[PDB]
Image (cartoon, rainbow over all chains, first blue to last red; front, side, top):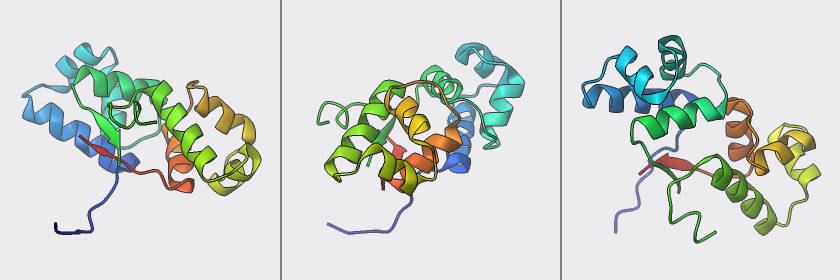
Length: 71
Length: 71
């Protein structure tokens, strides 16, 4: 039962997680923005790790089927 | 808790997670707010699931030693 040193999410890596999930689902920023109910600009801000309201982030996570949990 | 950490997170359950973790460490709202570098009022907002900036949430999470990860 190998005990490894991994890392928790911060603001930047969350954006990158979102980006990777959007890309793996073959969705453009426009389409994903449509699915998540945000503007392309907002999605772009989030993927870049720029500060927004948590509600926006949860809309994005929910729209892309990304689940986050407590460690 | 066990109902919150055995499910993916939303805004409300995140706030409740913060609250419970704070309570398990025997911390008042003032002290925890102090530890996290936010106001008591802000911590109260987050624990109640009210909308704030993601940076604030990450400050609270980091200050209380709560790690979140991708599922």
